[PDB]
Amino acid sequence: NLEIGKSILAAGVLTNYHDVGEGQPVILIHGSGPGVSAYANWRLTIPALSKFYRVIAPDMVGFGFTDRPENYNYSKDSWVDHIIGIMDALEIEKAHIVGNAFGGGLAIATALRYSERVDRMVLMGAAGTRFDVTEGLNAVWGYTPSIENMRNLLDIFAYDRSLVTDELARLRYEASIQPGFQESFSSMFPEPRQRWIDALASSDEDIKTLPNETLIIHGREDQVVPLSSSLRLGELIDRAQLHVFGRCGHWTQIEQTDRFNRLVVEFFNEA
Amino acid sequence: NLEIGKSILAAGVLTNYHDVGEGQPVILIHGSGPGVSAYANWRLTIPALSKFYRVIAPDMVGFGFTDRPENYNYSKDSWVDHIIGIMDALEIEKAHIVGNAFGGGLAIATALRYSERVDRMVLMGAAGTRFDVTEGLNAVWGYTPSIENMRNLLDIFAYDRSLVTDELARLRYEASIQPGFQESFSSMFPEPRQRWIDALASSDEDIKTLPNETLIIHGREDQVVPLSSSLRLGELIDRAQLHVFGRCGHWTQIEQTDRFNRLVVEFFNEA
């Protein structure tokens, strides 16, 4: 299973992660769908970025193959602590961070609590602002295992449905039913789900204080997070650029891979 | 005067233009401020793009050093005819087009009337949609010569006012009072100016038919054209990408030169 990588103790949690490349460190933080993992999210991103940077992609506690501690208290702050724990464990003093959706909210929160540890940020279809729950996100977080339910989620995630094959739905369905995966997932974001969008968000006031050069990315047709949310982040963060990809969903790094990798690498190259 | 380049008869008008580089043709179309010219608009863009493309930057009839025919009938359609005349005169069968503001509206109109002649488009703080006249545009089109009035316009155009020096204001003021310049300019967009924003715009219906890969660029702080206009173009044009530069005004190619040139060259490189 290529989704399983290296193992390291971080913030007291045995963490699964990938580490490829040399040089300036870049932390990639995945989304929050069923069966999600750092590899599943970043398999097409790591190869490109690792040619110029040291890329670290961990499975956040509660997701992927990282340990799911008994009675663990999941929260925006606990996840931020995990990210910092991972950085501390790897002697990463300061790094750029690419946060995808769920991960984007965590990236913002980390930059706010540990400003000295974050350099540049890339926020893709990111959590971070309070936006009305979408049917897309409610469906994603309300997932129940089945190849048909997974196919529907994959359809929700991408613009070009021709990319959603029976094989992909099958493979992601299988990933979603691995031991303990669905159990922790279904209990992670229970109804009413607006609560978690709000809990993962940061205040307009706080976001305005971010001094980091930031690149906000969003797919025009994103069904999970409305473009309006990223437009808002683009107005709040001072040193920000906003790039909207037409004919693209909530899976920008996979749907517009080459354009995405190019934009991100050049963005970090400026530093 | 570096603003004066080569001369060619196009659409029956003696036209001043610049032509640098080899390969795929790219037409750069300037904005509509007082004293504007292809060189003034594109001096920092041509050098970069000409390394990979053949860059053609003409002074549109009524502007710069191109002839201002007696009793000439200026209109969106006449300007489109000039662009096509320039392309015909240079045996340019198909080309990419970069339209800045005024030029962006002309680029859209050209792509609609001569679809077979336009490949990819870059629209920066572009005309093309009906948006309520801004004080910025009304001030630009309502310019009366003076170093103070020019300084105010330069301030309106850029985000970083530290770039607006006494020398720059002086030089652009001088450009605005060249023989016949102010006379044709003041009679070009008379009050009520909303009429010209509307005349230069294309219908939502027509814009939706554009099949061209398009890159829409806008400075977050643009005081002349509201970001909302470019957001609209980003929703209407199917194969579009929208890139918003924070800490940037209506002069993106000059305010964020390296980022701009990089994005544009890579955009054309995809073709």
Image (cartoon, coloured by chain):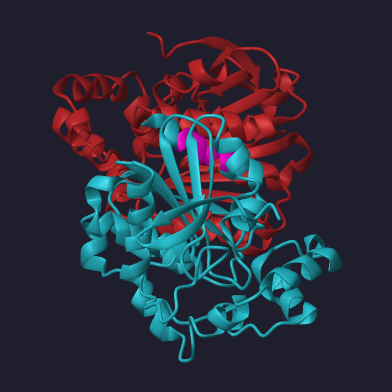
Chain colours: A cyan, B red
Task: State the image coordinates of residue B76 (x, y, percent, origin top left).
Answer: 57, 44
Give the extent of the magenta segment: A261-267
User: Which residue is at 80% across, 70% downward?
Assistant: A170
In this view of the protein, can residue B73 be seen by the observer? no
Q: Main secondary structure of the magenta part?
A: helix
Query: In the displayed structure, would residue A180 be above or below residue B245?
Result: below
Comparing B95 with B179, the one in front is B95
Corner quadrant of residue A45: top right
Tell me: A255 left or right of B171.
Answer: right
Query: In the displayed structure, would residue A77 be above or below residue A217?
Result: below
Say which quadrant the C terminus of chain A sits in: top left
List the single residue furthest toward the right. Answer: A166
Q: Is residue A68 magenta?
A: no
User: Which residue is at 50% across, 65% downward?
Assistant: A227
Q: Is residue A262 magenta?
A: yes
Tell me: A118 left or right of A7.
Answer: left
Tell me: A25 left or right of B21.
Answer: left
User: Which residue is at 46% across, 57% downward?
Assistant: B229
List the single residue furthest toward the bottom. Answer: A192
Query: In the displayed structure, would residue B214 be above or below residue A78?
Result: above
In this view of the protein, can residue A253 be seen by the observer? yes
Corner quadrant of residue A248: bottom right
Task: State the image coordinates of residue B66 (x, y, percent, origin top left).
Answer: 50, 20
Task: State the image coordinates of residue A102 (x, y, percent, origin top left).
Answer: 47, 66
